[PDB]
């Protein structure tokens, strides 16, 4: 149904602005809010239908100590949204405490938007893990949202902070945030900073301006993830029906994404399926094995070729995953959007549950434990101090993420009747 | 064939004969079944068409 | 049939002047009394048909110690009415006692006007609750009118004094007036000062000159309430047929009103029905539930759309009321008046019986009881003293309004077979 977006963190507000700009360009919308002259397709999930058919984006921007919001302010696209949903230290506990005291008015804004919406389906989160101000306050808001609304869905888009080092206290912050994400979120879309950075340095020749490109990448991914809802077909035109297949168990809810063209500015679907199963098209980094794989195709498709392609790729066994049970690949189809020039119009997406990200989490589990053992890297922050004088919440999150890694490695085994 | 497909629009009938009747659209159908959840889960011995038509109008 | 208007209180005489000016502008009437050059429609209820077709307003102005009446006197609209119907302390008991001694000649004026009218239907009252001089004398006249004419109708338009404070004795006065209004009136149209003040500060940017705007608001409301009589259709062209549906029981006779444009200087009826059910279009402030709702529409209406709109709004269930029985919404239609420029010509009104005003009454019941308990706020007024040396009439009104609130809360329950 109707989904409200929340955006917080500097990179999160960047990709939210880019996402809304991308959808305004994608649909028949002017940057004033007015419907375009040449506008069939649904805008009834993320866009409020206002008085002059003004598709006002259903978005709530949360920030504290604004810097980039001023750059949002002086823009022609500052008249598309902001019906006054904008509300004005780099520690987790700092942002937690600051969000604690102003929980009421921002929750009042959320309830205001819930009253403004006729229906409700979910709150999708734009998040940056260990982004400083975004950390802690984002976990706090996630806990509040799970508390107040036990009937709605929570989706999280976030990047995982790895740049091969910087901040000595960020693994603690990301660990607490991951503990909150495991318990207080329903489904998590995971992203890696170094992986997207490497792809940006790969297909292009940039080294510094990675933000401006990665905004485009995440915007394309997120819009692709929502295209079958935005452009109505009839397979999984609800969020919940899509998410139900992707989550095999409530302990594994992290989703790996790709994108079939690394650059798209006339191959068949058979080729790009083979491309997508190659890991260079995969944008998120014993044997690691998928549990369940889904793919979504949008382009110029012949309907017989997808069947024979599934036959041939099935027989070729390019799906290097061994499950513990009956779970298999799932196909889906979406519409190519108008008004956008696309060479090689076939474009696909993948949503798969893969165990390999455990190793990435294990990297942080190694790092944090190392800095815990030497104990010269907690640095004695005061917000961390009165929030927890004994710092046993870090031990609690360490317990949870250990259980999580064990659940991962039990899922790697060909039986999940045994647990980890 | 010319007069049949313009004065009576024979082809529009097929296009709406898949999308709706053969359940070819499904934005319509999921909301339709959603609104028809509490009514159709109740036993249909007390079901009369006038309760169906009015909620059908809102759904369409 | 033929209705005579009575106007008393400073704000009541203000809105009476504005109402008569509005109807003179609305109909083909010059401000001398002469029919306009371009004048089909009925003026045979509130306008006497005089010698040169002079539609002389059937109005009786009652005042004591005149101040604003002098401003009425020097006006071009002082020749429309006043065929000598004008007849020259802020306590309830003061105005009661003063009206007591001159009851005879004003009753003689009333009988004179009754003889002047061929038929009679009702006396509609322009009243200001706790307006000082209007209080007490208005209750006295209401009691006299109910006594002398047991065959006629009494309608009361009045505002309820709340400005969030001022006068420490006004809750006593309004309580006695409410006791009289409950027993000696047939139907009451209730208005709130702070609500209309808030709407005036909302749609405009005024803070002081609220009177001049609120006159327009009440005039528009009252004229809208009478339009189907003034502009003849055939549904409820009598007062009594209209009032019969609105009153479900003789204990609940207070009517909530709205107005669909907050400002009207081409939406369909479906939209403005949804607007009218939003409380921002409603001008009067467990669950509070309507008993019976009526609406009146005047504009450019398609007759099939009202049926399908009733279907869709019925199915959407935007009528957040739970009755105890079979009572439902009622639709009505009226004519858009000529000679008045109207953009978005569709304009509607609502008449509904809602329990929420009990809480407002409860606010006064709290306040008066508080000032009764401390007993430093009766102030020992002498008119109050010889009128009642023991002040048990205040206890009597407290008894009645307690019974009234209990009747309200028994009506809130899904059975009214039990009483309160």
Image (cartoon, coloured by chain):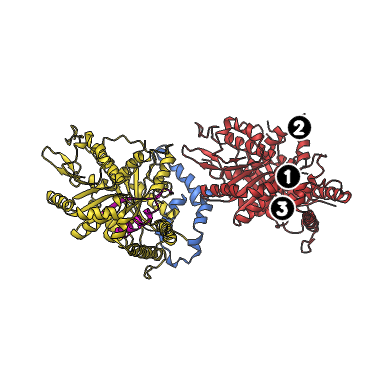
Chain colours: A red, B blue, C yellow
Label 2 or label 3, whichever lies nearer to me, is: 3
Left or right side of C178 for A206: right
Q: Residue at x 31, y 54 (%)?
A: C92
Label 3 CA crowd tier, 10 Å (few <14, some 14–19, many 20+): some
Name the residue located 50 percent from the left edge and 54 percent from the top edge: B32
Q: Position of residue C191 (x, y in %)?
A: 35, 50
Mark 2 highlights which residue? A203
The first of marks 2 and 1 along the sequence is: 1
Q: Are marks 2 and 3 on the same chain?
A: yes
Q: Which residue is mark 3?
A: A180
- Disc 2, disc 3: CB below 8 Å? no
Q: Secondary structure at mark 1?
A: loop
Q: CA distance from mark 1 to mark 3?
A: 11 Å
Q: Which mark is residue A129?
A: 1
Q: Is residue C33 above or below residue A330?
A: above
Instruction: Answer whether residue C156 is magenta in the image.
Output: yes
* Residue A416 within the magenta-colored segment of the rendering: no
Q: Which residues are magenta?
A: C155-181
């Amino acid at each position: 149904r109707e989904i409200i977006t929340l955006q917080l963190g500097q990179c999160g507000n960047q990709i939210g602005f880019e996402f809304w700009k991308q959808l305004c360009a994608e649909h028949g919308i002017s940057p004033e809010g007015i419907v375009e002259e040449f506008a069939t397709d649904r805008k009834d999930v993320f866009f409020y239908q206002a008085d002059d058919e003004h598709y006002i984006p259903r978005a709530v921007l949360l920030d504290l100590e604004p810097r980039v919001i001023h750059s949002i302010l002086n823009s022609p696209y500052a008249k598309l949204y902001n019906p006054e949903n904008i509300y004005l230290g780099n520690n987790w506990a700092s942002g937690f405490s600051q969000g604690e005291k102003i929980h009421e008015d921002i929750f009042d804004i959320i309830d205001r938007e819930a009253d403004g919406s006729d229906s409700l389906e979910g709150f999708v989160l734009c998040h940056s893990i260990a982004g400083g101000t975004g950390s802690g306050l984002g976990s706090y808001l996630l806990e509040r949202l799970n508390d107040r609304y036990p009937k709605k869905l929570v989706q999280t888009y976030s990047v995982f902070p790895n740049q091969d080092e910087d901040v000595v206290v960020q693994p603690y912050n990301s660990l607490l945030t991951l503990k909150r994400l495991t318990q207080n979120a329903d489904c998590v879309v995971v992203l890696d900073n170094t992986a997207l950075n490497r792809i940006a340095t790969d297909r292009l020749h940039i080294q510094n301006p990675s933000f401006s490109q990665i905004n485009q990448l995440v915007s394309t991914i997120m819009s692709a993830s929502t295209t079958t809802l935005r452009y109505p077909g009839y397979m999984n035109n609800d969020l919940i029906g899509l998410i139900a297949s992707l989550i095999p168990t409530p302990r594994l809810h992290f989703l790996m994404t790709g994108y079939t063209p690394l650059t798209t500015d006339k191959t068949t679907v058979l080729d790009v399926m083979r491309r997508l199963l190659q890991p260079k098209n995969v944008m998120v980094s014993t044997n690691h094995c998928y549990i369940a794989i889904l793919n979504i195709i949008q382009g110029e498709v012949d309907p017989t070729q997808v069947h024979k392609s599934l036959q041939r790729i099935r027989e070729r066994k390019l799906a290097n995953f061994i499950p513990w049970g009956p779970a298999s690949i799932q196909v889906a189809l979406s519409r190519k959007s108008p008004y956008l020039p696309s060479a090689h119009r076939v474009s696909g997406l993948m949503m798969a549950n893969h165990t390999s990200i455990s190793s990435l989490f294990e990297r942080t589990c190694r790092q944090y434990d190392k800095l815990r053992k030497r104990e010269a890297f907690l640095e004695q922050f005061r917000k961390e101090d009165m929030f927890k004088d004994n710092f046993d919440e870090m031990d609690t999150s360490r317990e949870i993420v250990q259980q999580l890694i064990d659940e991962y490695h039990a899922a790697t085994r060909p039986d999940y009747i045994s647990w980890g | 064939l010319d007069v049949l497909n313009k004065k009576y629009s024979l082809l529009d009938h097929m296009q709406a004969m898949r999308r709706y009747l053969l359940l070819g659209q499904g934005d319509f159908i999921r909301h339709l079944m959603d609104l028809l959840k509490p009514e159709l889960v109740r036993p249909a011995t007390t079901l009369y068409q006038h309760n169906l038509t009015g909620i059908l109008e809102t759904a369409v």
